[PDB]
Image (cartoon, helix red, strand yellow):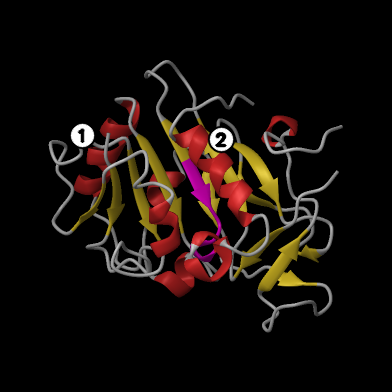
């Protein structure tokens, strides 16, 4: 029972920065601690979830093994990087995700028409929920708006499964944006890649039913009454 934000890879959001408002909703059920030194399989001992909010330094094949072990051990991981993907972020995180069928592309999602927000990349997505059960908030068969700021789209193929899309009014249209991996009886290791680290920051989490989305992404990671 500890949630671990990674911070030595020059992450964009660490516990010192950024995801300040996200922590308040987690320090309720968890012990949030940052990570400053190299990832050692022992270090991740208590950890229920490891998080990288927008890494910007490369990873070492040594560090990767540390994580694939940790994921097959029943650990959980959450990787979020942003607009422009690995080509604006200078990090080799894809080498790890490529094994689970997820790969963060290098493009930015934009809006169709101006509403509420300054920048074109502050994309507002009305019908992006893909799995029905992810309406673990209300609605069934109503909509769910979230603000998808400064983000890239994911290439998702099995075994991973896409669960949020850019929608029908953002561009690229209908391309995956959040992907999950539960597979195998490892048992029950869980990975979740999000196409943008900003979606959960203080700047946007409060704003547009992003908060319900967070709740669900974290109940699936931190399982959780969620089953696709």
Q: Which residue is mark 2?
A: 160
Q: CA distance from mark 1 to mark 2?
A: 26 Å
Residue at position x 83%, y 73% in the image: 112
> Residue 225 or 174: which is nearer the viewer?
225
Would you call the spot at circle 1 few (<14 residues within 10 Å), some (14-19), or many (20 or more)? few
Residue at position x 58%, y 40% in the image: 216
Question: Magenta residues?
Answer: 192-198
Circle 1 or circle 2, nearest the eye: 1
Q: Residue furthest front?
A: 28
Would you call the spot at circle 2 few (<14 residues within 10 Å), some (14-19), or many (20 or more)? many
> Residue 157 or 13: which is nearer the viewer?
13
Element carrying mark 2:
loop
- Give the percent coordinates (x, y) of residue 191: 45, 38
- Horizontal arrangement in the rendering, residue 205 relative to residue 143 (left or right): left
Q: Earlier in the sequence, mark 1 or mark 2?
A: 1
Residue at position x 71%, y 35% in the image: 131
- Give the percent coordinates (x, y) of residue 194: 53, 52
- Give the percent coordinates (x, y) of residue 204: 57, 67
Q: How many marks?
A: 2
Residue at position x 36%, y 63% in the image: 55
Element carrying mark 1:
loop
Residue 31 within the magenta-colored segment of the rendering:
no
Q: Which residue is mark 1?
A: 46
């Amino acid at each position: 029972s500890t949630i671990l934000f990674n911070a030595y890879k020059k992450e964009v959001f660490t516990t010192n920065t950024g995801t300040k408002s996200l922590q308040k909703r987690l320090r309720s059920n968890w012990k949030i601690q940052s990570l400053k030194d190299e990832i050692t399989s022992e270090k991740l001992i208590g950890v229920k979830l490891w998080i990288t909010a927008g890494p910007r330094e490369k990873f070492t094949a040594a560090e990767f093994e540390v994580l694939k072990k940790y994921l097959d051990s029943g650990g959980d991981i959450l990787v979020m990087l942003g607009e422009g993907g690995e080509s604006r972020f200078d990090t080799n995180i894809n080498f790890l995700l490529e094994e689970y069928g997820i790969m963060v592309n290098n493009d930015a999602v934009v809006r169709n028409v101006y509403y509420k927000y300054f920048h074109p990349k502050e994309a507002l997505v009305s019908d992006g929920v893909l799995n029905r059960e992810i309406s673990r908030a209300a609605g069934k068969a109503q909509a769910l708006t979230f603000v998808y700021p400064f983000g890239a789209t994911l290439s998702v193929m099995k075994p991973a499964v896409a669960v949020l899309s850019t929608g029908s009014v953002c561009f690229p249209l209908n391309r995956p944006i959040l992907a999950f991996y539960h597979s195998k009886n490892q048992g029950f290791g869980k990975l979740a890649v999000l196409g943008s680290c900003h979606m959960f920051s203080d700047q946007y989490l409060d704003k547009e039913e992003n908060s319900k989305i967070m709740d669900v992404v974290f109940q699936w990671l931190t399982t959780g009454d969620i089953h696709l």
